[PDB]
Image: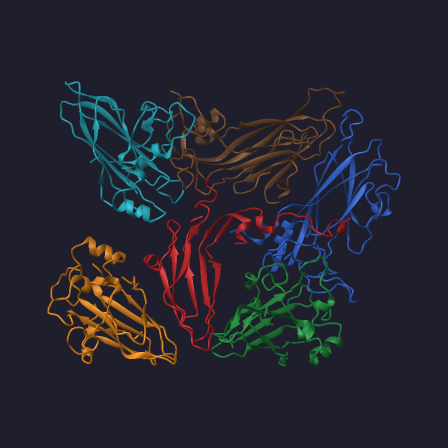
Chain colours: A blue, B brown, C green, D cyan, E orange, F red
Amino acid sequence: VSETLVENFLSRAALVSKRSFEYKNHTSSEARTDKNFYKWTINTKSFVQLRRKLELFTYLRFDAEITILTTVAVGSNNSTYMGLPDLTLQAMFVPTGALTPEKQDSFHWQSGSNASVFFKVSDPPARMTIPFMCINSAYSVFYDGFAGFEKNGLYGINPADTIGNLCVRIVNEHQPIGFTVTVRVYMKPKHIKAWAPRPPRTLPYMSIANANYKG
Amino acid sequence: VSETLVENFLSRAALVSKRSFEYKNHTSSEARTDKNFYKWTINTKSFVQLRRKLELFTYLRFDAEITILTTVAVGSNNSTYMGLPDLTLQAMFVPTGALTPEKQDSFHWQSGSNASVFFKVSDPPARMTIPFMCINSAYSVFYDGFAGFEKNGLYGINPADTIGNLCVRIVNEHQPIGFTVTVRVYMKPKHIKAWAPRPPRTLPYMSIANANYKG
Amino acid sequence: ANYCCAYGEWPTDRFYTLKSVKWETESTGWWWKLPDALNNIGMFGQNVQHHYLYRSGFLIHVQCNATKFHQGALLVVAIPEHQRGAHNTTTSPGFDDIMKGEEGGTFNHPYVLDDGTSLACATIFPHQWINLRTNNSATIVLPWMNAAPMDFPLRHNQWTLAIIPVVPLGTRTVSSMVPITVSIAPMCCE
Amino acid sequence: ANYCCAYGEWPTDRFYTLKSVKWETESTGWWWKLPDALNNIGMFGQNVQHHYLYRSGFLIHVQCNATKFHQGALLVVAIPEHQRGAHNTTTSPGFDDIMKGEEGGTFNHPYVLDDGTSLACATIFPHQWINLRTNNSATIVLPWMNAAPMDFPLRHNQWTLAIIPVVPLGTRTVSSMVPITVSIAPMCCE
Amino acid sequence: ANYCCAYGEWPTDRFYTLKSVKWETESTGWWWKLPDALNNIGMFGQNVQHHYLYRSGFLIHVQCNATKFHQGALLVVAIPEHQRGAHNTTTSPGFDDIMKGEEGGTFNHPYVLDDGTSLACATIFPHQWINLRTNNSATIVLPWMNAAPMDFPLRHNQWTLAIIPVVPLGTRTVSSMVPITVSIAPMCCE
Amino acid sequence: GNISRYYTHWSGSLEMTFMFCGSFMATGKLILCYTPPGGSCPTTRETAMLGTHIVWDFGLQSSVTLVIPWISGSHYRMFNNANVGYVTCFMQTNLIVPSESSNTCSLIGFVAAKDDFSLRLMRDSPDIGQLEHLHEAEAAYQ
């Protein structure tokens, strides 16, 4: 009977985001906002498995534990194997109401208020636990309301919640040889409390922001 | 008298499976299901030593501890030694009743329900303990019955038991230089209980699924 | 008379009676978003647009007027945070088609609850059954139902009362009509 | 009379007597799979094909009818989960050659028990010896013997009663015959 | 619900429900001979043709399904040793026209009970009245009713359940139909 | 079913409730029979009457509850290479309705799990509709 508790049912690590990015000597304006870094707003309604599992409840309250797995490889083979040089990566958690970096060398990377972790590729995956970041007592999986006070607000978007934004960059100044690095983010909710269970989703999802159904 | 207990007699790590696989830029359909990954159904009746030792009993109940040892080498020598780049490998335990991956980039690799372990080649061997996974109270080493309800069922195959399937892949996207990696799997039963001892096997085995004898 | 306390929680007496709806043999259902329904009527509406704040429960009474020769079944269900969805587009529902006021709206696809979920599993929500051969009334008591201790009545609908005919109304004549009366009594309205 | 409780466990009274088999000087042995033997006879068989389920023990009595001038030794052994094997092929035994019913089967290679093990070590199983110069009967009591608490009688044989002449029957005449009678009494049959 | 113990004697629970009969405005009546009705159904029939012997009572439940706009009266009477008779001949009734099985038979002359007696005096037997304006069900409990302590179920019918419409069924339409359901539950069946 | 598809092994007993949604004066009888897993689904009323059955008179009772006995779905043929038991309904009598009522009546059925239900070995539900990429996904977290 312990396996079917809500905590065990929902507290499974899942690949919430996976996004590789090149870094080769990006002095020019090639691939703006993708030169040597990527950003990802921390939203749980990204993969359909986790969407359907979480949308079984109306209100949720949990702490998200994030583990980042990074791999480096190259297909150019312009020289010998020569191994892969050890790169240090910076992952900064930018909470809501704070400024997120727009470029790899932006001064926001050294804010001193946003929590940041520095880890190497050869090191084990970096782990951090994001606490319950909401002005309300629980996240709103479904929100029968409008965000803004004006009528142009979006339906279903709670201006509360909004856990934050996660940005990852390569700390090392661009080495002579470019490289492709892939960062995998795994989120595992912890200390989960759930309220008001709901019927399971039956139709395929149409969007990440709407409850629209096909049929 | 302690050395000759059943737990000490059977709880010895053994090379249950060893299977190398190439990974060189397998974008094409070369070596389907062997492109960059291999799978192995977890069965104890694979090596004759362990077969004869386990078939001394009718019913067994144990937890299997799996240690994975991986080595990388190349005989091509197309360039300098240049060392061996550190690759991250994913080993996913797919229990019975779940879908196993069919390709290296299948979405089953990020299921979020199948337990998975990520380890590097330079790291010590990865260890995981698979619990007693059976709907019955003990595994059936010998089964005087038929699996399916129809008469076409196989003799001796218990639809229970069936510990699960183990799949190992290289997480890194294919690097410019191909490589041969060999994964060795060692299984060591723990907390073993045995019932109904049986006469030892005397004739050479004819198959992994039958008790057929030559002579 | 045999009320249903939602989620086993028991949190004035005006009982704002909305205009009765006509239950036909081809009706799909009706829904009212509770804060929005009373936003434009009575001391509740006056206080709601006087203040920026609101906090209260609700009391729902649904009654049908039919004879012993009528048949049909209704599902009276209160859905918390019933975020609706569109049918064949990726754009979110608009303010006009979400905030229907005291008039309310009708279900386009009662089978999927206009949400993409299943009506068959809607019984997990606080609900009552109106089977015309056994009963004709249903009463539901609704708690606060908000994550925050405080709320804005003009932007967020905490509850959505839905009445869906599972078994269509029927009689000897091919055309049938049975009035349905909905009365909402906010309790400790702020 | 001097019964043998298998594995020291003691878990109706119909005593279904199978047709007697003839013990000749060249006989290799006989075996019966216990759930299958009674699957087509008596209230046991009727209940077995009435239900999808079965759970009970067994009582086995084996008796020989011979004179004081006969010689021979029998091994009456009950093998749990006696998964048989083929002799010169890699294909598994079939349903026809596994489920022999109340008729039973004969050992092709009693030396290896048709399993590839040794007959000499078969005494580890619950067994009794019938030496014609000392005794002519053997009784074995069989427990539940199943990993699961429940079982399907039509697909899985939990026990296999085997009678193997270790010492061939002999007398002054070159041809000898001694009847062997097997009686099985399921206890608490389900 | 308000059962009738025959002759003030109170002597399983399967309640074999026979196929419902249709009560029309021109129906004369239906009868079932109790041992014969269950002789070919259920564990009662299996035991009856397994043994040469039988001894038990009976429990009878008769129910009608009609609306408040239907009218009619039924006499549910259990006749012990209802030896029938022919209408215009001196030959005795045959086995085929006596043993009707679970199908039962119909009254040719309900006025004389197919016996030559009077229906008006049939109330001396254990009976119940089904007047559609007051009740729609009748329950009778039948004792052993045999001179001998033992009986042969395949040759002698101890009871005969008879349902006779004294007042014909009627409604506004000239054609009326009301199902009648008969359930028999032998008690302590042998 | 939706929750159980998230797990591999399920065991317990189910409870079914059937509600008659006809007119007030509609009358009739129905037979609800339960067939154990090791049996064949009945095809005729008298064959169904032999087994465990309930004679439901919906002219008197508008709702009937049927309790399915404890069943272990794990043991009973889950890809052992579905006749796990049936619940069937037969019309014992005709449907009788007053002239002013409708000629057709409907039945509503419910299912619930008793407190003895058990679920084990959680897996990935296949009824999600499979993983398709959704709209506004990439633009959400550039």
Instruction: Tell me if residue B213 comes above or below residue E56 in the rendering.
Output: above
Say which of F22 and B140 sits in front: F22
Q: In percent of the image, x 34 and y 45: which residue is there?
A: D55
Q: In percent of the image, x 46 and y 41: which residue is there?
A: F80
Return the x and y of residue E33 as percentages of the image width and height. 21, 66
- Residue C22, quarter of picture: bottom right
Q: In percent of the image, x 47 and y 67: which residue is there?
A: F106
- Residue C178, quarter of picture: bottom right
Say which of C50 and A20 sits in front: A20
Instruction: Tell me if residue A110 comes above or below residue E93 in the rendering.
Output: above
Question: Viewed as shown, does residue A132 lie left or right of E123?
Answer: right
Q: In percent of the image, x 49 and y 26: which residue is there?
A: B47
- Residue D26, quarter of picture: top left
Say which of C149 and E15 sits in front: E15
Q: Quadrant of the N terminus of chain D?
A: top left
Instruction: Tell me if residue F65 comes above or below residue F96 in the rendering.
Output: above
Return the x and y of residue E72 as percentages of the image width and height. 31, 79
Return the x and y of residue A127 as percentages of the image width and height. 70, 43
